[PDB]
Picture 1 (cartoon, each protein chain N blue to C red):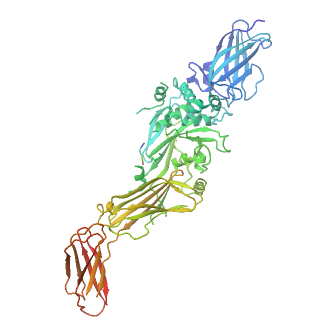
Picture 2 (tube, one colour):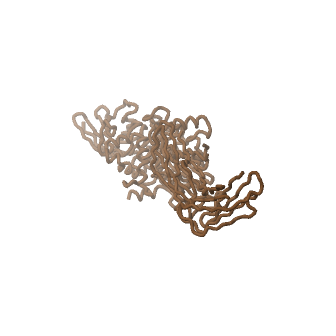
Picture 3 (cartoon, rainbow over the protein chains, first blue to last red):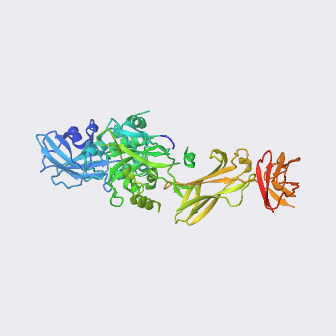
Length: 4
Length: 611
């Protein structure tokens, strides 16, 4: 999971 | 006639476990599913049961404050007449000293741990006493159960299977992590019950909570809010390959969905893990890099009817155990019916995002939320794409009609007002108009940076963030950001340009508005007056110019270029005047051509026509  | 003496009760773990699909849970204690008959065999010491002489009555209680009105306590006789949908007991076999019984629970019985009691009565005398315990679970096999699922292979997948895939990676590189839900491992069913027993609604009203456990909607809702730890514990607090270890240790990103799915499969609610993919200088990305947007996002779907809602909302319900949320029908998300409980708008925003350009009004496709929504195929090791369940095809009348039901016209431009000049401070405005009957609350990013003529972005020379900007219906707003000379001078480019950018976020529906605009800080204007011609220039800076020099030429007016220096430095605001003699070569129009030069302010140009 990673911030756009 | 002497009273009966039970020697023992046989819980028929084997035939019950197999018929109730709880074999793995029926290793020690009895576990069954509601709305379906199960079996007990009484072995008496001495004479057997004689329907004519003995009346037998059963009592079941569940929870810490049982009642009949709440459905958490029942008394029912042993008789041949069996009433459909009620607690009943009936003899189905009678041998030497044994008595085979068939018990039925209502299909809407609260799930949980049950104490089973028996009162043996010979009219003139009696005696009550406990037989034992069974656990009652949801029944996707029972036509009358809320969680009913008409398909055997789906029942296997969404309740019975203990390993699956959770999808991760990215919309273009989908990665399938294999997971061990192990809902039927030792101790797991007991933890799910404990979890239920420590949720806030239980602490608030134990009795009512145990009653409401008749509802897969209530139970799923409770689970979504228990996987995470909001100061009240709480399973997870924000590598490993399954849910078992996590849950066992507890008793002493995709992980939330995985644990939720474990619990709900254990309680008998058909459930699936789903992954949603999102994809991406741009104020948006900048803004991101408390609800943000990630490359992917995981939640669960559970299968149930929704008698608590209007008709037609049975089937898959979305529940998000991510840091209570749901359940909300998936069709309500797809249909933009966000009024529907529970928590429609929140789920809607996980799969929709409306991004609009005002670059002066166009559609910005630099942010794309809701792609390749995914979940494991039934009974096969492959991915099912369920994007269609959440979203009508882009550009369709259903997609548009749905956007309306959801949204129930807001616009943004960058405005300047008065004139801006190299050397001065001045406001720029995000001008927001709201010609709707809706009231909004947005986040606002307003910011400026220098930019070359080629389009290369220098350093930031102004920023204003507003977490909550209120927009009244049928109204507008001019939101100021003050650009300071003190702040852009040092970082200015040969361009002389500043780029203003605004971002308005409406979080609920997940809408975005971008307005962008380059501004030119114009040079001072050279005044040319003919008397001989006089040329002057006002220092536009709050600072003093060192080494001022003019240059004047104009064929038809001077045969010689006249470069005059300025000895003293010119102070802030202080003007500087020079004069030179001209001897008009010929007759008609001529153009005088002027250049001004300085250490800070260089290469400013001017002209004047003559005759």
